[PDB]
């Protein structure tokens, strides 16, 4: 940076702290990643100055010729990446992408069937303190209490009983492959739309390491900042038959001016994802997650569903008589960042929990491999088996530092 | 830029076109401005990598110590700038800022009273194709058909008749000072909340050139990218008594992860606005708008309300037998960017219109003054009085080029 240090010493100092923090810690938040310098440059461009309500070639402001090129690059590369008939790259966030789809096909009070929030479902999949659960009548399907895999007979029974207008598949904390074919079959049975929220798994889908929801879903929503490794924002994919309706839902429905600089950054991230090396990266994410899972089991930890098919895993800490809150706190003390997480049929509140959620997307981006996964698991074991030993915690601290250089 | 040119030639070429476009054109879109290099650097920072759901010191993710500092700088500087008891700097946009306030105090189907959309009111103030008009029952107050000033007796009558739960004041195309005291008096009479959407005038308010709505309104919403000259986004100001409710409306109500890099950029923009030179700038914006108004009248143009008290003006093109659409198109041909705009009691559709909307915030930022205002008015006169003369249009083109260097 050149201008920020002089203009705003306070903001610059805080940003610099954050930058150094991102290098020093072992970042295991499943939803996080590190974007490229190109992506950041796009976000830091003069495109923030441009009002561009509407869509390419159909704007409500003149002078959009070039931001049109940018948005179209984003849309076309997204369509290449996922094989979708239509893309809307304007959603400000995952929240707004989901909001727009709901706005398109539902009226206030309509019944929607989503994943149980304590079993992996997201806040925007029906929380009663979120717009989703306040605006619409959400019911939930669950995972099997033993396997922790989605119970498709439960999905089917809930759908047949409650007759939702929309079924939502996908999750913020589900460590196994989702069967989109079965979701569509159930949706077809009850005459419901199917929406898939692939936010967490979007990069994996792009790399062919998770089945693609696009052929099975009427709508696919996603964020651009998780496994897709792009800027912070949302996107909607859909068949051509819903394109007009989806576009109208975003604008003039639920948003105004799009963030053209962020859309530029989306285009850049999609360009990166189209490359062979992104596919290799995504494989290492999944490989690393399996390795970390196995290594954690070797340390004596129980994992939700007994492992992982994707980028993320959940540790069930009940055998160690620890809460997720306690584990999160102590791992923070040694420089390892995780989330506390509710496990299926968790006896604890969502504010305490019996689990931690871990993902490998971020550490994989920084070049961590299988050996690093073994060491991360060993450090977690050292810490969680010795929460009362300051010497153990200091050793962990030193081993964390050794990993991050 | 260093990394974008190599990584993504296509995106870089389009951004470069846009940058050069921003220099070449006379940008008169009332809602636009040019942000500083510091603001852009903040947006282009690694803060995009950080999930920070929740609020400073009360996050749902660890490792937020430094992004907390950034958000708090934004909130505290906003409170300094506007004298508000509470700020929420998380809204992704003006749309979401407004959405959050509505979510806080209204239930589905509640009556809201806003400014007539063809008289200056915004899309999010009750359009039937926007969430506002679909989710809530909007009624409208109008301006006087002769003076084009808000008819406060009409505000009062509509409020007393329809008994709204919320009254919205403020506008996307109102060229005069709004009387917030009178709005609060009417709101008090009918037991309604008052929300002021100061998006357009926020920079002017910060510089003491427009009365501050904060003391009169229960909620004040704004964008950060118009006269405030910040990054693209939203903000809500309110009294302490609504702070918890407003914060909960943004999260977990209507959004997820905030854009921490954009929040950094907001902090920077607020820092700039706190400086003496921003106050001088804002005065020049208003001075330039008055000068441009007077110069346009000298050219024989009729202005909505007969002039301006702020950054923007509307030309009523009916005396010239031109539509706003025609004027917008031909001005585009010579390198002047305006919007077509509905005038009060416009005989034309909102897609054709009888007016153009012009603002001086952007040209003032690039250093234009009173002499430049005279020339801009003279060029507009030359063009709009000679729409069929290619030689006149080429002369205009050359005079536009002379202004932008």
Image: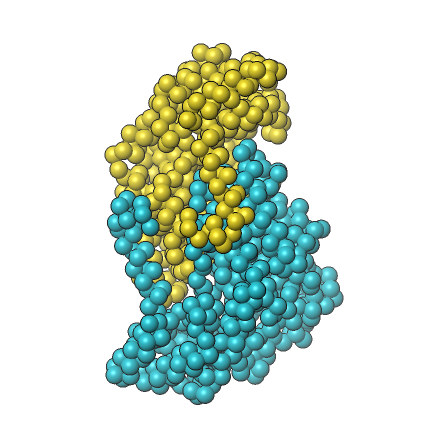
Chain colours: A cyan, B yellow
Q: Quadrant of residue B138?
A: top right
Q: Position of residue A75 (x, y in %)?
A: 60, 50
Left or right: residue A56 compared with residue B155 = right
Determine if residue B129 is in view.
Answer: yes
Q: Quadrant of the C terminus of chain A?
A: bottom left
Image coords of residue A342 (percent x, y): 47, 73
> Considering depth in this image, is A166 or B20 the residue closer to the camera?
B20
Q: Is residue B77 visible?
A: no
Q: Position of residue A351 (x, y in %)?
A: 41, 70
Residue A55 location in percent, x, y?
Answer: 59, 42
Query: What number of labels is visible?
Result: 0
* Residue drawn at point x = 43 percent, y = 27 percent: B404
* Of B324 and A202, the residue lying toward us: A202
Query: On screen, B47 above or below B10?
Result: below
Q: Is residue B160 left or right of residue B230?
A: right
Q: Is residue A214 left or right of residue B254?
A: right
Residue A16, above or below B11: below
Residue for point 40% across, 23% down: B289
Seen from the viewer's position, the closer of residues B207 and A77 is A77
Can you say whether A234 is above or below A159 in the image? Answer: above
Residue A385 in which image quadrant: bottom left
Q: Residue furthest front?
A: B6
Residue occupying the point 49% across, 54% down: B7
- Residue drawn at (66%, 58%) of the image: A83
């Amino acid at each position: 940076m050149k201008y920020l240090p002089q203009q705003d010493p306070q903001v610059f100092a805080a940003i610099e702290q954050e930058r150094k923090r991102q290098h020093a810690k072992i970042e295991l938040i499943a939803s996080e990643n590190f974007v490229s310098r190109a992506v950041m440059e796009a976000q830091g461009s003069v495109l923030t100055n441009k009002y561009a309500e509407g869509y390419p070639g159909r704007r409500y402001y003149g002078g959009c010729e070039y931001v049109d090129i940018v948005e179209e690059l984003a849309r076309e590369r997204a369509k290449q990446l996922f094989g979708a008939e239509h893309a809307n790259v304007q959603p400000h966030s995952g929240a707004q992408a989901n909001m727009a789809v709901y706005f398109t096909v539902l009226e206030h009070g309509d019944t929607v069937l989503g994943m149980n929030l304590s079993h992996g479902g997201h806040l925007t999949h029906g929380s009663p303190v979120n717009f989703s659960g306040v605006q619409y009548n959400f019911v939930a399907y669950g995972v099997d209490p033993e396997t922790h895999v989605i119970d498709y007979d439960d999905v089917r029974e809930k759908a047949r009983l409650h007759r939702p207008k929309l079924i939502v598949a996908a999750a913020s904390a589900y460590p196994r492959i989702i069967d989109f074919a079965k979701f569509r079959e159930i949706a077809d049975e009850v005459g419901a739309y199917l929406m898939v929220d692939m936010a967490h798994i979007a990069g994996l889908v792009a790399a062919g390491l998770h089945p693609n929801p696009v052929p099975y879903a009427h709508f696919v929503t996603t964020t651009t900042h998780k496994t897709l490794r792009g800027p912070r924002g949302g996107m909607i994919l859909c068949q051509e038959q819903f394109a007009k309706q989806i576009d109208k839902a975003i604008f003039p429905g639920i948003q105004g001016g799009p963030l053209m600089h962020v859309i530029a950054a989306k285009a850049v991230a999609f360009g990166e994802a189209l490359q062979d090396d992104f596919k290799a990266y995504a494989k290492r994410v999944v490989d690393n997650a399996k390795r970390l899972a196995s290594a954690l089991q070797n340390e004596g930890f129980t994992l939700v569903s007994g492992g992982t098919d994707n980028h993320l895993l959940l540790v069930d800490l009940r055998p160690q008589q620890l809460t997720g809150k306690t584990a999160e706190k102590v791992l923070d003390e040694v420089g390892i960042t995780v989330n506390k997480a509710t496990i299926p049929y968790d006896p604890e509140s969502p504010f305490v929990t019996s689990g931690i959620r871990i993902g490998t997307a971020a550490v994989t981006t920084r070049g961590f491999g299988l050996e690093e996964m073994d060491e991360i698991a060993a450090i977690i074991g050292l810490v969680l088996k010795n929460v009362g030993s300051e010497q153990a915690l200091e050793e962990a601290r030193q081993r964390v530092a050794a990993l991050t250089d």
